[PDB]
Amino acid sequence: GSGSWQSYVDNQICQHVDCTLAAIANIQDGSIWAKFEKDDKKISPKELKTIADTIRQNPNGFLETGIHIGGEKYICIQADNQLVRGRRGSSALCIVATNTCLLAAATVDGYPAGQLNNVIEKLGDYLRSNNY
Amino acid sequence: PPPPPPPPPPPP
């Protein structure tokens, strides 16, 4: 109980990753808690509902369907209960699931994917360690 | 609606 989820998105993710898209949501509903959208991108609550339910119930599904966020399709490169990574051209996507939260961000074309992965996975590890 | 459940203090 300090600060807000928008601080996390605006400070912990967007200040360390050059993002087209970032979101934190409820892992159970998909209810969006904070977000960032660049230019003409938008995160449907339905995109996140399905993402949230797929990562928790059947993460292998992303390998079949791909990943749908910001109104665009990303190719899945790996998927499990806690971590899903994706590609769309020169843009990377990293999605993490904690005990209560879903984190997601995607990168401006050409931005290093390891840096996004590190930022999202380490923030997820911090939250998970706090039982969030 | 209510605020969502509050985040923990930011990481280092």
Image: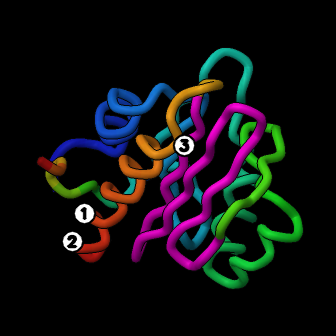
Q: Where residue A69 sits: x, y (%)?
A: 73, 45
Give the quadrant of residue A53: bottom right
Q: Residues within 10 Å of mark 1 (few under 14, many from 20)?
A: some
Q: CA distance from mark 3 to mark 2?
A: 21 Å
Main secondary structure of the magenta stretch: strand
Label 2 chain ID: A
Viewer-side residue, B11 vs A113: A113
Q: Which residue is mark 2?
A: A130
Q: Residue furthest bottom?
A: A57
Residue A111, compared with residue A98, is above or below; it is: above
Left or right of A119, for residue A76:
right
Q: Where residue A14 sits: x, y (%)?
A: 40, 30
Secondary structure type for disc 3: strand
Left or right of A116, for residue A61:
right
Contact between labelled residues 2 and 1, with CB atoms less than 8 Å apart: yes
Q: Residue at x 31, y 72 (%)?
A: A128
Q: CA distance from mark 3 to mark 1?
A: 17 Å
Specify the color scheme.
rainbow
Compare marks 3 and 1 and give the one earlier in the sequence: 3
Does the magenta-highlighted stretch encompass residue A86? yes
Q: Which residues are magenta?
A: A79-107
Whether labels 3 and 2 belong to a single chain: the reply is yes
Label 1 chain ID: A
Which is in the foreground here, disc 1 or disc 2? 1
Does the magenta-highlighted stretch encompass residue A52? no
Q: Residues within 10 Å of mark 2 (few under 14, many from 20)?
A: few
Q: Residue at x 60, y 21 (%)?
A: A38
Q: Which residue is mark 3?
A: A105
Secondary structure type for disc 2: loop
Residue A113, compared with residue A56, is above or below; it is: above
Q: Amino acid at mark 1?
A: Tyr
Q: Residue A126 shows which numbered tag?
A: 1
